[PDB]
Amino acid sequence: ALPPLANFKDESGNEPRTLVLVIGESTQRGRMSLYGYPRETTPELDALHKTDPNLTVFNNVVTSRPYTIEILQQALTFANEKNPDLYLTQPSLMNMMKQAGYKTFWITNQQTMTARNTMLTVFSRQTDKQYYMNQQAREYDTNVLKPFQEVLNDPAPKKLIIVHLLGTHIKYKYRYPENQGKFDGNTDHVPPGLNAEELESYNDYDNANLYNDHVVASLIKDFKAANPNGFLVYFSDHGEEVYDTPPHKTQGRNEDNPTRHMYTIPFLLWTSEKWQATHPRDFSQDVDRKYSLAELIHTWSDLAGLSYDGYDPTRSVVNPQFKETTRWIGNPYKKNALIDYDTLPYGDQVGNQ
Ligand code: NA
Image (cartoon, rainbow, N blue to C red):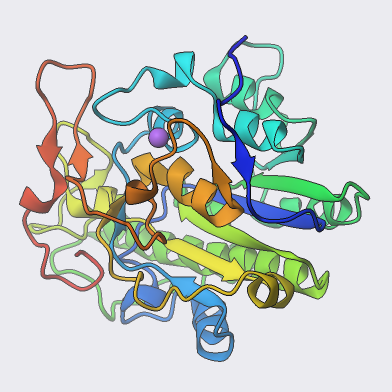
């Protein structure tokens, strides 16, 4: 029902390309070894970072809200903390890619109620083809690998593939097979004072991070094996507090009682050899920019070569005109409840910038 973006231009040429957006779940930045966590929770992404120069790891990206649909309404559209309702009145990322001539796909391991009017159902239905892999629980994110490959074989020249993961969502133990609890009973690098149940939950979160590492690295590896022209962006919708913050008694997500570990997120960009060769771009000076996921659509636009009325290059984290703005958190529907993420304590801790 919304009109297309005005003065729409695509400067990325007309060669076929495949662009991938991997939406993880409840994965914070501070529990991945890729970001300095002393437990080896992400070995495959670490090795990929060591061996592949086209993997760009962003170190200072946070989400704006710690609830899935509440953040995705901002990340996937032009809405943000100051204007949270723009997802109703302006196009989404998927709409934008359709206007650019892409065939769009939604692959998900999250239980979607297709017969019901949920906001996630609407977003996934904004694409040309959907793969609902979890419609009924032990359904692991590797479920997405088979349809992903299938979509890679789809003959459309320009393709957008969205992969929605369960990631490290509660309950953590159910995110990975029972025989893959590498950190079960381990007490190294554990905060003090946990009881048996809290300790088991902590180690469960690290195990879920291990499996999520395997899944994301597998997506990148299979994508690369297709020898594609394009790139893949991986981000988590939000983090998750798992006894990280002193006094180490809190587990979960609470917007009105925020901690940094609820808001820090991984943010990775893998660029294929063909795309890097055809679209030369240096990201090495962008990796430490302080950025909020709420403006993702501009970064994506920048990466896709798209410009239009409403495009803001200064809010793209890969743009030379990038200008840091306040990384707002807090409920945007309460009266003047927005606060600067930087004001939260314990910002000096590893992975908690
Ligand atoms: Na937005």
